[PDB]
Amino acid sequence: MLKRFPTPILKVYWPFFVAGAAVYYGMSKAADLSSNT
Amino acid sequence: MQLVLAAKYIGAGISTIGLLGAGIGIAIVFAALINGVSRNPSIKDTVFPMAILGFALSEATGLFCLMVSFLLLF
Amino acid sequence: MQLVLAAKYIGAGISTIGLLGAGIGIAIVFAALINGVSRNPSIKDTVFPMAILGFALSEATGLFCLMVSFLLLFG
Amino acid sequence: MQLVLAAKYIGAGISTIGLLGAGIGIAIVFAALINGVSRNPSIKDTVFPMAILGFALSEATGLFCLMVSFLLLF
Amino acid sequence: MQLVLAAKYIGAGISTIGLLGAGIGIAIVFAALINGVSRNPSIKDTVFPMAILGFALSEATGLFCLMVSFLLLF
Amino acid sequence: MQLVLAAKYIGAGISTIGLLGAGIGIAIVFAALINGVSRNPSIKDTVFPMAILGFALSEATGLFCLMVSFLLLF
Amino acid sequence: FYFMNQLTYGFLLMITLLILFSQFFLPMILRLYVSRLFISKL
Amino acid sequence: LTTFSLYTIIVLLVITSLYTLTNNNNKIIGSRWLISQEAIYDTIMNMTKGQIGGKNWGLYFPMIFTLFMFIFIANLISMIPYSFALSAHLVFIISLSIVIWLGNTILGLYKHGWVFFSLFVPAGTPLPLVPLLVIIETLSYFARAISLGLRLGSNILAGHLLMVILAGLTFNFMLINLFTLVFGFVPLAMILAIMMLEFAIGIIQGYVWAILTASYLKDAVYLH
Amino acid sequence: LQSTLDNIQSARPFDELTVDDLTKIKPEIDAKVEEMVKKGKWDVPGYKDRFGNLNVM
Amino acid sequence: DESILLLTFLGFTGLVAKYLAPAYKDFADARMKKVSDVLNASRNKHVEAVKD
Amino acid sequence: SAWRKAGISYAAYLNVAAQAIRSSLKTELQTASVLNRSQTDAFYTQYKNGTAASEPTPI
Amino acid sequence: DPVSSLSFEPSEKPIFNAKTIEQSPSFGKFEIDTDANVPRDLFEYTLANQMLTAMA
Amino acid sequence: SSGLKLQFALPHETLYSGSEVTQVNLPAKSGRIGVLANHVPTVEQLLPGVVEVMEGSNSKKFFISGGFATVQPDSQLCVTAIEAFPLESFSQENIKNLLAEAKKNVSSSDAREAAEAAIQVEVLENLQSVLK
């Protein structure tokens, strides 16, 4: 199919993943504070 | 309903002044036409069909604007 | 209801002059076109499709103007 | 209450003409594009995205008005 | 009270078109950009860093009035 | 009675678009920066503080305008 | 309404395409680059 | 089940349908379906090679690839008339911009820390506007954040709904009296021009997204 | 080298050769590809000269 | 109401098959012949180098 | 001023400029190369298609 | 053209009129004012310099 | 280049020829133009005035009788002109003014003489700024 290569996405792309989790937590705050509109 | 025809009248009033930039743009067209023929008299009426064509379709914007004002009167 | 369609008509009135920059815009494009052939005669057929590119998308913005004046006139 | 929907309509109308500032702006980009190539024919592909990129930055500003109209329309 | 939100609707309408000249202005920076490299090809990736800086600052003029439309929307 | 705060909203609407001129203004403070420094590439460090001088104290006047809006909103 | 829905499935498919295009679709063409270069350079 | 997540599944099926069926048995010659992907890879490669210009420039080159392609593909499916809006969910696209901006700030603070706050002073200026130049910077610092998202979906949401309501134009023009069929060819060409605009407002706006966040990558990675 | 010339004579699939056959004939290809990914020199130097980038810009 | 945008889509794709398809056809054919010609010529060149 | 219409060519414009500059000389510094540099001694004679003659005038 | 002190050459030098100067392909590369008659004077300057070089 | 190659050339003595220079300052058709180490390839006709050449060393002050400044695109600026000039020694007021009055008199003659004498009055009055 396609030759899988261990291309660096964990030792390079950590802070955007951290930001995605933090925005999920902010959406937890928002959908528990401003989803009852 | 005494207000609505008068509002159509003032709407045709505010929808009239779109020809301001139409006249400005066609003046800039003829201004660059003079400035182009001043530096190129040799090519005068090859640019000028293209110049007057762009003039035509570009003033047609303000023409459509005041005929919108015409149909808004009616 | 004795006031709403009248305000719709004057809202179509104020949304008619935003194509002002149509009547400037494409035209001053042509102005540089007249410059472009003047200082460079053999570039004309080079630039005029690009300039007609510089025509078409350049005027359609003003189209948006009167289609607001087409909608609030009718609906 | 019979005015607030009319206020939405005329507030949409005064919000509309911001695309004017697009419709002039993009033009001089194209005009500069002609003066990107009239004085320099060998560089135009260099500016062939780079001009129209600026188009997409100016056009969107006009696109940031009428939909500000539309949320007041709807 | 049916009138105050009507007035803030039309206040969002008038606070829309402040993008206008900014929607011009970014373009005129781009206009100079097309006259930057077609004049000077070997400054192409020197000015284009700061010019797209000067883009965003010219955005920073004509964007916040836009969100004055949105906060007066709510 | 219902107009004393409704009119503050429309005053905030009209009293914000002054950045419009800033959207025209500082643009050429970049744009004449471009065709200036494209004309002379090594004037850049000579002029880029001066330009960012001539940016800032020419911008903040427009930043006063919506400030007059802000106190008129609160 | 569907803020959690769109946001969560968008997060999943964003990180999915991140790792997917990274491990697969850029080096599958970089192989073509290095192959054509190594044949042309011999 | 949601039609939106199903649309994302259709996106991933097209992603399968861009390279596997493209590549005839791993051939050197580069067939016609692969030439377009070659051109895309090169026009992103040579772009971000000159954009961020780093010694470590390629290290985010896949990211600047894959943040583009999502907007490149999702504005090829809503182009269908009988479709629902994919990227016109402004909460989603603006939240994507929030994620990218916050990842840039965490990258800049993990790479530089306190000297990452040295970005607030662009040039040496005389005294009575030294802090003010910071403030308009900070005023632009979230405007660096907010606009790029609030400038993509508001494009697309302005487009197709246009082609909804102007379809209503053809529901308001070709339903009045029969002489509306006379010279009624110009709304057809007008909607044709709007579709010409819509391919632009997808593709070129996705490239605008890519180039602006590439500039923001040079901002966050390199302190001036 | 006469056998090398005869090998070049009848074994040139210059329109149908596989890049997996190139990785099979040369694992140095795979090594340079993987190292080129892992270091992050995503530029391919000395390619654009004879093999143009054929992109939009 | 929605099939009229479909009619514009069908007419536009007909214009695409009229206009855009032979241009991209010729671009792909030109790049195909160019890459194939260079890839054959480099091989023939170092075959001649082997002969030298 | 209007030398382009009425007076000189631009080469001759700069020639008259050089004659004025070397005419504004320091007489200590006005060497023989200066005066020989202004030693206008060329004689022009307009011929015709029948090789006729004009005056050999001092240019 | 004195090729040496002991040799020589009768040599030709072309002069391009100012009409050709705006028509030149590698000419818009050089920035020039349209409003200063720079080709129509630089052609005269070219004529003067090439005459002086030919004579000397 | 770091700096610039100045080719300052005259019919009697080409003074600088690719001399490495930081700044040239020259009266051209658009006025006094200062050009640094880099510039657009640009052709300018030069009005007779004061050229100030600043280098790694100080800035020299010469007078020029007009000519051409041409930026060869390798950042080689060629000044091609006629007259060089010292600080102020070649300039003498009694030489200039007594001739300038006679040149105003010859500017009343026929237009072949009058235009040229008007040019000469212009040049001597520009040289009055060199008298300074």
Image (cartoon, coloured by chain):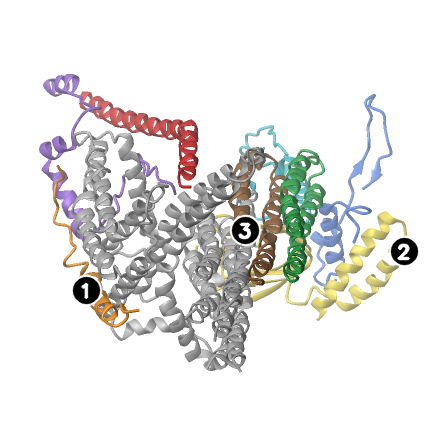
Chain colours: A orange, B green, C brown, I purple, J red, K blue, L cyan, M yellow
Left or right, residue M90 beside residue J3: right
* Circle 2: element type: loop
Residue type indicated by callout 3: Phe
Foreground mark, 1 or 2, reads 1
Residue corresponding to mark 2:
M108
When the figure is inspected, residue B7 is found, relative to residue H36, above or below; the finding is below
Residue corresponding to mark 3:
C74
When the figure is inspected, residue K42 is found, relative to residue A37, above or below; the finding is above
Foreground mark, 3 or 2, reads 3
Whether residue L49 is visible: no
Estimate how packed mark 2 is, as few (under 14), some (14 to 19) or many (20 or more) residues with alpha carbons within 10 Å. few
Compare residues H109 and B69 and report the one nearer the observer: B69
C-alpha separation, residue under disc 1 versus residue under disc 3:
48 Å
Foreground mark, 1 or 3, reads 3
C-alpha separation, residue under disc 1 versus residue under disc 2:
90 Å
User: In the drawing, what numbered circle is on residue M86?
Assistant: none
Label 3 marks which chain's residue? C
Left or right, residue L40 beside residue H189: right
- Residue H221, image x and y in percent? 28, 63
Compare residues M1 and H172 and report the one nearer the observer: H172
- Residue M88, image x and y in percent? 67, 67
* Circle 3: element type: helix
Q: Tell me the residue at 29%/58% (across/down).
A: H92
- Quadrant of the snapshot with the C terminus of chain L: top right
Residue M96: quarter of image: bottom right
Q: Are marks 1 and 3 in contact (CB under 8 Å)?
A: no
Label 1 marks which chain's residue? A
Residue corresponding to mark 1:
A21
Residue type indicated by callout 2: Ser
